Amino acid sequence: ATFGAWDYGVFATMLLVSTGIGLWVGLALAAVPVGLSLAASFMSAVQVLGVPAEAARYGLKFLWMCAGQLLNSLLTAFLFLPIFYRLGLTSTYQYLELRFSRAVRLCGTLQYLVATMLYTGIVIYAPALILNQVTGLDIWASLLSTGIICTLYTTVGGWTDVFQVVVMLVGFWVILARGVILLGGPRNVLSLAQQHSRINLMDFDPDPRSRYTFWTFIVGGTLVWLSMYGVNQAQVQRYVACHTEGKAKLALLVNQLGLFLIVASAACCGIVMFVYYKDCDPLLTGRISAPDQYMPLLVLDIFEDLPGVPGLFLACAYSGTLSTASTSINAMAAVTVEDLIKPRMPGLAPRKLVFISKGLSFIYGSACLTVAALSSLLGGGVLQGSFTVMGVISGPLLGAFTLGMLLPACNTPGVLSGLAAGLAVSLWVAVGATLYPPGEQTMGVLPTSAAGPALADTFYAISYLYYGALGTLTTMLCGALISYLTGPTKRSSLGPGLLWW
Ligand code: NA
């Protein structure tokens, strides 16, 4: 029910060792490692908690997420990697500089900082949620602990990604292997899932309100993962540092393979989790309050006769998530210093520049902890929360980049107005859904079992995967229209720039 004795020791020892190695790194590349770094940059305990739960509650439709990811990678390697290897170097928003203006560069950097801050807040909340659900500590003590450890990793801590990805994969495989053997027979699990309508691959429901479906997954995942891989500063930084566009596409391929493995393993583990709870769903029984508590519960249930392992898995999912959060915070600080402060403070006390970078890292860590606390209080849903954070905020940024590249007739006022309109629409739909969320029947939640305004109904029910796609598209539409209203930009006035070349 709540770890025990051996698994408490396992959790504590593993977390202490992880902190020690982090401090050692902070005090004391090839396509494959950098691609696995690309994969690890966005996979954390959020995906451990959410993907199995979403698969269990909807059923093997979540595999279509992989397809979305696939599209993302392809588009990147064919739309943004070539241009961010010849035109936009060093930074990603320098393209917005040399294309539209420095004002658009500042707008893009601010959007990236806000999106990353909120995403890292959700990321920090995920291990806090794991600790609260497992160890029993109230969510606020768990948030205090996770924030303290993340700030220790960032301020003090200053192949780790490969280790994280392999740990995620092995954990998922161990869970879904122990579950199948305990239940008895992979064929039996598949048959039980089929009976309870968990094998639902071919879902083409054109209704956007249906939370998960091929039509929703392809477009929404493509757009969100593009905003997270095609224009994200960290990912593009990892591209341009790969030393070759052709060898950067190899990194993207490795990243895509890692994402495929993680998502497939998580969905299969979620199906095993449901078939484990085929007759008595914990949600109906009240054993847990939110679906995000599904994964920590099963881990406790499966290995009740095998102490220690739950602590190992849920301490790996803690340390890896904290490493991801610290990398995000430090990247935010570095981006702020390099892209904003340095231009207006060119040669003032490089030691002061290091001091300012440290201060920004601390400020961003604190802000991310505050966002984690807000997410804890402000309802729940971590996988949807992260995709609505990276969707509404960064979606318009991807729209700005795509308008700057694809459309020759795009101008600084055009892209700025498009960004404003896209942010407005995306936040409008997000708040409408938060206040007036759709029901389980509308979204498409599969049946459970316990035997052991017109606008708010037609729009706010839109699948969360459509938030980002709603923003980006808006930025591409409005930004285009205003461009042709104020003044169409001339192809001659642009350098290589546009993908058309
Ligand atoms: Na996510």
Image (spheres, rainbow, N blue to C red):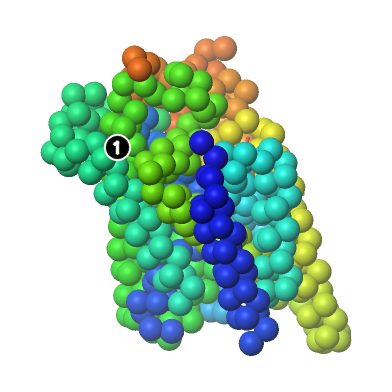
Q: Work out whether residue 139 or residue 388 is closer to the camera in this orientation and state it.
A: 139
Q: Work out whether residue 186 or residue 41 is closer to the camera in this orientation and state it.
A: 186
Judge whether 320 appears above or below 395 on screen.
below
Residue 75 in sight: no
Q: Is mark 1 within 8 Å of ligand 1?
A: no
**Left or right: 482 with respect to 462?**
right
Question: Within the image, what quadrant is residue 90 found in?
Answer: bottom right
| Residue lying at the far top of the rendered structure | 453
Q: Work out whether residue 468 or residue 357 is closer to the camera in this orientation and state it.
A: 357
Judge whether 28 appears above or below 252 on screen.
below
Judge whether 249 appears above or below 196 on screen.
below
- Image coords of residue 484 (percent x, y): 54, 49
SS at mark 1 in the image: helix
Residue sitting at 67 percent across and 54 percent down?
146
Residue sitting at 23 percent across and 25 percent down?
197
Question: Within the image, what quadrant is residue 254 found in?
Answer: bottom left
Quadrant the C terminus occupies: bottom left
Residue 436 in sight: yes
Report the number of numbered marks.
1
- Image coords of residue 67 (percent x, y): 29, 50
Residue sitting at 73 percent across and 58 percent down?
148
Kind of residue at badge 1: Ile
- Image coords of residue 251 (percent x, y): 36, 74
Q: Work out whether residue 20 or residue 407 is closer to the camera in this orientation and state it.
A: 20
- Image coords of residue 364 (percent x, y): 73, 60
**Left or right: 392 with respect to 195?**
right
Dot 1, how many residues are within 10 Å of its Cα: few (below 14), some (14-19), or many (20+)?
Answer: many
Residue sitting at 19 percent across and 38 percent down?
184
Which residue carries the number 1 mark?
Answer: 271
